[PDB]
Image: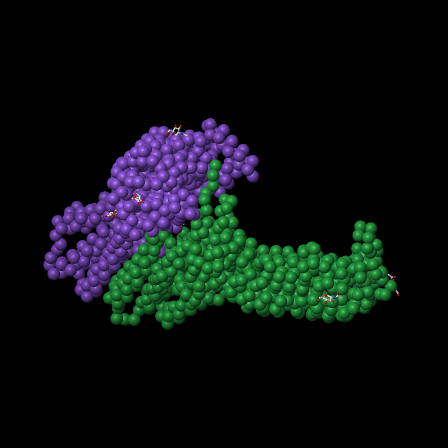
Chain colours: A green, B purple
Amino acid sequence: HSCMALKAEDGEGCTCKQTKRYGQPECCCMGLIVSQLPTNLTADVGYLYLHNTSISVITPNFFDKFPSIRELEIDNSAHLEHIDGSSLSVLSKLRKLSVVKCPNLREISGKLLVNNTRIQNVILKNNGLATMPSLRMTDAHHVLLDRIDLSGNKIKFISDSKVRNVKARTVVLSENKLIEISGYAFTESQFLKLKLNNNPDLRSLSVDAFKNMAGLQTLDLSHTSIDTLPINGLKKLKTLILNDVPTLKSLPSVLSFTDLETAHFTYPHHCCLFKYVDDVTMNDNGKYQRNAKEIHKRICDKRIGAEPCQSIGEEVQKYYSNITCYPQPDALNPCENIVGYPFLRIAVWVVCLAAIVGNIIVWALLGIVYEKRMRMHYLYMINMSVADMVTGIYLAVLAIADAKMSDEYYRHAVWWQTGWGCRAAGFLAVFASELGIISMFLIAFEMSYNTRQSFRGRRLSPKVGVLLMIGGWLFAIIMAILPWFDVSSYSESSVCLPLRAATIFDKSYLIFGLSFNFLAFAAMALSYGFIVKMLKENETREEDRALITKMTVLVVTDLICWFPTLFFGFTATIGFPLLSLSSAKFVLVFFFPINAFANPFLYV
Amino acid sequence: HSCMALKAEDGEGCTCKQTKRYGQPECCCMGLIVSQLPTNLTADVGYLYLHNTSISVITPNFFDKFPSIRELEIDNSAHLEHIDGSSLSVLSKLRKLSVVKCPNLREISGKLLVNNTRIQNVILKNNGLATMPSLRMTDAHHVLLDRIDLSGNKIKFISDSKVRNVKARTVVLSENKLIEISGYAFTESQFLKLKLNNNPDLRSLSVDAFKNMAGLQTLDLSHTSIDTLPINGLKKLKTLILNDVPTLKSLPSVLSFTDLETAHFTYPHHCCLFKYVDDVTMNDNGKYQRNAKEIHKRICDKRSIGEEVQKYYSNITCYPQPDALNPCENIVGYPFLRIAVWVVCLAAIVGNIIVWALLGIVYEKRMRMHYLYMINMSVADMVTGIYLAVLAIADAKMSDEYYRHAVWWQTGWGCRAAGFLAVFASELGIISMFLIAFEMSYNTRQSFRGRRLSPKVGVLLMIGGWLFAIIMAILPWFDVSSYSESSVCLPLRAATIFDKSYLIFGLSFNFLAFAAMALSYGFIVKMLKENETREEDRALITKMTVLVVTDLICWFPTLFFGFTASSAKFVLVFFFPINAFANPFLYV
Ligand SMILES: CC(C)CCC[C@@H](C)[C@H]1CC[C@H]2[C@@H]3CC=C4C[C@@H](O)CC[C@]4(C)[C@H]3CC[C@]12C
Ligand SMILES: *[C@@H]1O[C@H](CO)[C@@H](O)[C@H](O)[C@H]1NC(C)=O
Ligand SMILES: *[C@@H]1O[C@H](CO)[C@@H](O)[C@H](O)[C@H]1NC(C)=O
Ligand SMILES: *[C@@H]1O[C@H](CO)[C@@H](O)[C@H](O)[C@H]1NC(C)=O
Ligand SMILES: *[C@@H]1O[C@H](CO)[C@@H](O)[C@H](O)[C@H]1NC(C)=O
Ligand SMILES: *[C@@H]1O[C@H](CO)[C@@H](O)[C@H](O)[C@H]1NC(C)=O
Ligand SMILES: *[C@@H]1O[C@H](CO)[C@@H](O)[C@H](O)[C@H]1NC(C)=O
């Protein structure tokens, strides 16, 4: 409160007062005037506080004047360049140490907290610390550190055996710019919760970085580029947190963990990898075979009467089932199966074969009905057949993937889902959908303009029609190739559809798609009405009047099918996952595929 | 191990060895030469083993000769006719009891397991018993029986009040020909887990079969064929697995149970009744109102009444969770989709009436097999409409109710007839769609040459196609496929080997017929382009060509979505009937 009284006085000086609650007096120094603490200062001070004094650098003998110090705090000191930790450590009875808002405090040297058996907690946050303090410890400390914090600093490396024998609950290294943690970074220490989150640049961890530790209850690595989690030392974690670490493709063996109860992973399939371990756990037959032999008794020795100990291959899975994982699998990211129900499997196979057969029918019957004179709309019908063929290829990819990956999907799931293959599948699907939409709109507009101007005596240029076709093709291609990048990812579904909306920009992409669907529906309705009016004005030819009738059936069926599409989208304004997303998938796989599959029987 | 080692040296005889580990000597007998009790024997038999023994009958004097026997094991007693439980009861020194592979054991008399508070296991494996032993444990017993087992046997009956207070942890009566279980079969017995699996013949489980017993933590009736389940006794039950029981469609309400922690059922609607009990719990209001008050007091001491009870029940997970193939509380799932199917069925029926009027006005006076083909296509459209209507009214009748009485609709007759109508309508429509193009092609080709298809042949082929649709529709009534596995009543199951063949053959045949029809119409249009027919036929040819092409466009996508895919039900219910009623518009 001495600092508060000084700030109320606004006098850049040191003021002290004695408190009866603790006996020792409290002194605070403040302002730019004080370059060093004045000599006429009491020595029995327990609590020493410094508000942005002009101390440029703490000398190795700076704090030695006052032996009875018990608490320290330094704040806002913009002039602090370097501090020698030894002089601070000479303070035997130092209970708490805090340093904040020092921007230029580039280094703290020496083995801190050594020879100081009374430290209770350390707070070092929002400082320009450019290297890890060399924290050592010894077993004399009667009270463990409540919290030791280095968050908000700029540390980048943790060399061999930097933090030894510290006994503490919470240790935090978040927000730092770590690039590597070397082997044996910790040693002999026990931590209740070690924090390593919000560290974008952390790529490589040494395989034995957490080896030789004396205990680690909970650990979190969220927002990290960790490639492979270390195997050793982590054999006792109660909880594991690997949130938002897309580089963590393949986890180390689930067998190694022994007592974990809660685990948050980034990809959902690791949850099933933990759950579906039912047949995997008994296969180790090594050191963890002994560990399993030991853990089974640990439960079954104490679990009217009671069941006997079932074998080490069933009770271990019974215990492992209790392990809760947050990215739980769903119908959109299923385990052991891609398509699931056998009816759907055989239906997908037959429908892929039938889509290919329909494209073949398009080719053959269009060649049969082909007129000698070049026609503008033959190319459009061919492009719609191409859209149908792409849909068939997408379903073929899904079918063959389900055929190959059956019964072992959860192991291979992440590689397929994030891999190049899923991006290709999503490209195929969305490109087919957009190509069909733009092709329907283009053929409707071309027929409308040709019919309308032909009766008046003019015509829309067929080269303009080809230009519109290539413009729509580029539209579909750019709509499909963009989600390859992070505008909207294909990795959020097991069938590679773009059910992605997290960055709000992906929401912009989906809004653009929905708006284009609405514009296509409105344009088709209006252009078809105008076509009906023009047909009322004048009649068409005969041998190609089959195509005119096909346009009329487009007038009917396109409106019939796209009318409930927007209605379902509007009724799904809540956007409930796994229900509205399924509706969107069904809409995409129905309504463009309507015309796509119709193409043979439509065009004949 | 020691007995087998001694037997390996051509041990066609009885032999004894004084093992230092057990103190008392171990004795073994082997070979058909041992047709009776041992010749001169030893009186200090500690462990007893008899393998492939030619013993004929057992009399209490057999064991009284050497009352020191502590463990017993009888194996491969091929000739063994009968044993008396009294003989083993007198041998109170016994702790182990094994009897295996007896091929013709007809009966075991007396009360086995009585008089002996030291037996720890009773392992009767494949004894072929034609009547179960009257096993009993008296009040004086104190050793926890580790396991009592009756493996593959000929136990046709359990009879009333058979078993008296057995204290075994696990009772296994599996792989049995049980035809009936009279009441009180396990009176006052205390069991931890009871397994009755793999007894197909069990069809008369009494209401008091498990009455008054001291309780079971788990009860297993896997692969039974029971017609009902008693309410009494199972109140304390902690685990009930009823996988693959096909006949238990009248399960008492989950409220009757009080301590389930895990349950298995073959029909997911039972688990939906578990979760949706929310409105059923308070409906009881009988003496079970007092029972529910008691259990609510217990639950609240353990840590509104209805919400807490339903949370507790939701904690009772069941493996057959509900699925999209049979959504609970509704067939339509959505109210907007309900009005959509209502409007499509109304459009179907109104269009059918309009088509009746149109056929009445435009019908040609002269006989025409073409008009017959059009009539049967209109009938196919009408039956699609009636299938739509019955599904819609079934949803309306069971609005919000589709967890009670759900099973009877799927299995009893409603789904059977509805699926019959649906598939018959679809197949008749497809086959008529093929026949009309076949008529067009045959008439087009032959008339130019100067011939015509036989009208009798055409009528007979139309009747044959009608019969093909009928036989395709009737088959899933049997076990070749199933209507039962969907609230929409469509034939969705594909599990059995024949089911996959049936389903894939149906779909592939439909699409192949459509492709062949398209090829035939391509031939027709090529002929028309090359040669000009008579104008009277030319107008009719053009009208029918437009009709067929428009019908193709309307029909095709429905099966595509039904295969590539709630919304599946919506599309099958909406777009296909839309084609069905839109096609006559293209007819006229
Ligand atoms: C489910 C909601 C969103 C949309 C439902 C679509 C309804 C309104 C559509 C689909 C099929 C349509 C019918 C299709 C064909 C014809 C013939 C034509 O002369 C117009 C009327 C009539 C009879 C249409 C009436 C409107 C109709 C019934
Ligand atoms: C501390 O910081 C302020 C703000 O930069 C600075 O102006 C001031 O001189 C320092 N001392 C006090 C007492 O505010
Ligand atoms: C120490 O002396 C300085 C001047 O030398 C004076 O301003 C200050 O108040 C003194 N402080 C104490 C605690 O005596
Ligand atoms: C600090 O501890 C080290 C540990 O080796 C010891 O050598 C040193 O003398 C101590 N210094 C003081 C000032 O107590
Ligand atoms: C029976 O008597 C024979 C001959 O005296 C003796 O050797 C043998 O040990 C006895 N027991 C058996 C089982 O043959
Ligand atoms: C029992 O032993 C006899 C004679 O050694 C042998 O023929 C017979 O096969 C054996 N029993 C069985 C079931 O094999
Ligand atoms: C055991 O049987 C004997 C006669 O065999 C009988 O006297 C006795 O009461 C029985 N004991 C028990 C505990 O049933």
Taking depth in this image into account, of A258 and A306 the one nearest to the observer is A306
Residue at image point 65% right, 57% down: A168
Q: Position of residue A367 (x, y in %)?
A: 26, 67
Q: Position of residue A386 (x, y in %)?
A: 34, 65
Residue at image point 19% right, 66% down: B530
Number of numbered callouts drawn = 0
Q: Report if residue A604 is visible in the image.
A: yes
* Residue B316 falls left or right of residue A549: right
Residue at image point 59% right, 61% down: A213
Residue A462, above or below A404: below
Considering every residue shown, the one lying at the far left of the view is B450
Taking depth in this image into account, of B9 and B304 the one nearest to the observer is B9
Considering every residue shown, the one lying at the far top of the view is B287
Residue A466, above or below B561: below
* Residue B370 falls left or right of residue A147: left
Quadrant of res A403: bottom left
Q: Report if residue B270 is visible in the image.
A: no
* Residue A296 falls left or right of residue A425: right
Q: Position of residue B418 (x, y in %)?
A: 30, 42
Taking depth in this image into account, of A445 and B496 the one nearest to the observer is B496
Taking depth in this image into account, of B178 and A63 the one nearest to the observer is B178
Residue at image point 32% right, 41% down: B41
Q: Position of residue B200 (x, y in %)?
A: 30, 40
